[PDB]
Amino acid sequence: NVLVGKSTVNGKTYHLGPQEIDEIRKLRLDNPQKYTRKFLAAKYGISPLFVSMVSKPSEQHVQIMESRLQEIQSRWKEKRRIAREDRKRRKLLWYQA
RNA sequence: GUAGAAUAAUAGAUUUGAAAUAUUUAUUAUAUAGAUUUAAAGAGAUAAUCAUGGAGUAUAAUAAUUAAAUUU
Ligand SMILES: [Mg+2]
Ligand SMILES: [Mg+2]
């Protein structure tokens, strides 16, 4: 197998209920730093994709991490910026087929 | 147009499927192994912008008289 998902290796599970899904949401909105996607996935035996599906982080959290991305991009040099645009175009060309 | 029906966005609302081939889907650093790429101090070719040079071209008094052709 190549880049296979864990659920695909061992099939999907449907075992969480409304109350613990709601409390997952409360934890995520409370302390996104302490209760990360991987932490919640480990705690509740689900996938980080499912955590993102059911929960939603805080606006402050997303704003600060977008700013972090902006800083990392700004610290780049000319060559890395061009290389990243090239990666984007190449990846887009993957799907045209 | 003294006015309405008539495309897409931009967002909004109300619904909507999923545990979503996410131990890499999007993008983000380090380390190891390996494979590579990227010059313009100047130059060639071509074109253009400035020159240089004076080939080529026109004219050889351009006044006036005579003659043929014209607006009123
Ligand atoms: Mg070059
Ligand atoms: Mg000259």
Image: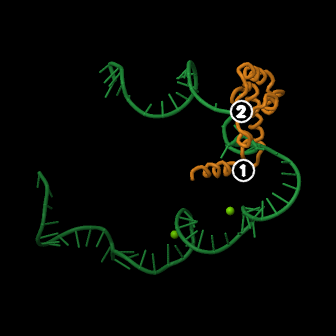
Chain colours: A orange, B green
Does the closest atom of ligand 1 sit within 8 Å of the Cβ of label 2? Answer: no
Residue that carries the numbered disc 2 in the rendered image: A13
Residue at mark 1: chain: A
Residue at 72% across / 50% down in the picture? A1
Neighbor class of circle 2 (other Cα within 10 Å; few <14, some 14-19, many 20+) is: few
Image: A92 above or below A67: below
In the image, A82: left or right of B1?
A: right
Viewer-nearest residue: B69 or A80: A80
Residue B22: % across, % down: 72, 40
User: Which amino acid, mark 2?
Assistant: Thr
Viewer-nearest residue: A70 or A37: A37
Q: SS at mark 2?
A: loop
Residue at 73% across / 25% down in the picture? A16
Image: A3 above or below B69: above
User: Which amino acid, mark 1?
Assistant: Asn
Residue at 63% across / 50% down in the picture? A89
Residue that carries the numbered disc 1 in the rendered image: A1
Q: How many marks?
A: 2
Query: Which of the two marks, 1 or 2, is nearer to us in this view?
Result: 2
